[PDB]
Length: 325
Length: 314
Ligand SMILES: Cc1cc2nc3c(=O)[nH]c(=O)nc-3n(C[C@H](O)[C@H](O)[C@H](O)COP(=O)(O)OP(=O)(O)OC[C@H]3O[C@@H](n4cnc5c(N)ncnc54)[C@H](O)[C@@H]3O)c2cc1C
Ligand SMILES: Cc1cc2nc3c(=O)[nH]c(=O)nc-3n(C[C@H](O)[C@H](O)[C@H](O)COP(=O)(O)OP(=O)(O)OC[C@H]3O[C@@H](n4cnc5c(N)ncnc54)[C@H](O)[C@@H]3O)c2cc1C
Image (cartoon, rainbow over all chains, first blue to last red):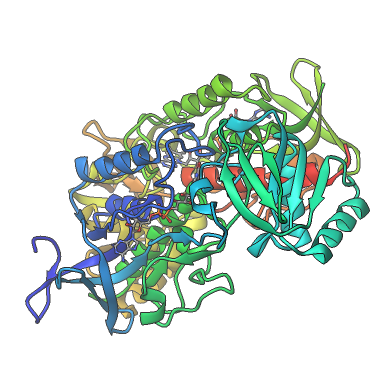
């Protein structure tokens, strides 16, 4: 290579291997660059929000393409700084060769990279509902985050909430339905064949201080989703032969962390599949390995991802400067 | 005038909070007295997508985004003098410097902090101009020094803080002198801690003489530190993270729990204060005083506000 310190195997050793060039990884690299620390940032080119044209709820970046944030971040990292190296390849394996001290990353081309520390910023993959038409409607009628979307489609007569998967409880369903009520006159909560749940959600709503006004409950099984002709509408085909048109649908899917690294490094995971990290610096259960962004928090958004990246760099700088080379 | 949220502050923290609320069509009045902690700076660093940009540009973009595409966020360029609760979590009243009152279901305090100067002649002249508080914020621009100083005074007067800063300053300078302003016991403790640490004390010097005054040098960001009676040392720049105090009387008026540093005590995931319905975000509510945490706090605060407004009666 051309940056870092030589090892006995013939390779150069950088301070940090950052696996990910979304906002989380780019923000981590941003902090390191301030203190002249070296990093190889890997990018497989798989971004969770690749299906979108417009970012929201990111201060100063309203309605901008998420690709623009990544481009600005990359430009900022190579223009006034020269310690940050970008590698467009997919990491297939990571191993700790020395405790907290040396890590090896191997890519899809057979090439090896060495860092004193590792940052996992691989993001997550959204798991589709096994229902016909779901894939056509995802991020195009079915929305997961009403801070991220929904405002553009406000003023509806009726929209739906899918109380399925992780939304199949009164807390999540009601929180999402009440958010949807800001955007629609009426909200129908779909339970896909769970009457008991529909009853639980209704009762919880009726028994809550604000009540159940504006809410509809649909317990019938869902046969398929059809992308309606107009705007972001989705026709939900229920039972044998009835259907209903909704302005759009709200569903926050189950996710899984991208890459095999939690398995390979035996990193503690959350019940939800996320890599378990602890504030203040978001170090994982193996020292010297950090995790930031979607792969390491239930707060899966751009501003928390960038914040995690900054704080991780603070911790990395501390470790790099306090620990013998 | 009753809105959902009275937001006191239009820095990154307040603006981020408003950005969140606007997505869900919640109403807010954002107050701005026009006093920003980084008012003295031309170049913001360590904020993804904004390297070397003017911090005023971030505030301008955040304001423009909110006024352009959203209609539920109001801005008031006035100073708030007093806030009080009218009914428990039900209602808050903010009184401005013109004797107008505003009512909100909730309140966000995003007032920032004021950096307390050292009581040493010449400090004021050298602040953010030779004396730097955050080596992620600055320092990189003045790299390649022969010598720089760390002021191990106030909150930096302990081996951990002094060594952490000194090792950061060593990235930017051949040598770092740690000043203890007359505390010889501290100088020795810092040296031993460095000497006994895994990385050692190489590149560090220790200066325990009392500091009489700071004189800003004519060249670049240099500061002449006047020691003893007549002796002096010229540094490339000095590094010191000051004690801070929250802006505004609101933590006192509402009797909000404070941290041991004087910040408003808040807790993730939503940064609500010790008084239900009052939130605090950004510098006034965290020891992590930087733009990206301030912005993230604003977003999460908006999530908690959104949750309460929609689960509680109007
Ligand atoms: C449809 C949709 C819309 C959204 N809209 C918004 C919005 O408006 N506002 C908002 O704040 N949030 C939004 N989000 C959430 C947002 O996308 C995430 O919070 C954010 O992208 C997380 O950033 P990250 O860096 O953690 O992961 P990502 O941005 O997904 O980046 C992951 C990086 O890791 C890399 N990677 C993964 N595995 C490997 C490997 N083995 N080797 C090398 N590289 C690897 C990828 O190539 C990629 O570069 C949206 C999400 C979705 C699905
Ligand atoms: C010299 C210097 C350089 C810095 N450089 C960087 C950097 O490069 N990168 C970085 O990330 N961070 C930097 N910081 C830290 C950064 O400035 C803060 O983290 C950030 O400004 C916090 O934002 P905030 O919204 O919490 O407070 P502020 O940005 O200070 O805004 C506070 C708001 O509250 C308002 N307000 C206060 N009291 C009242 C009242 N009574 N009525 C009405 N309104 C009121 C003010 O008018 C203002 O609008 C720097 C700080 C300093 C001092």
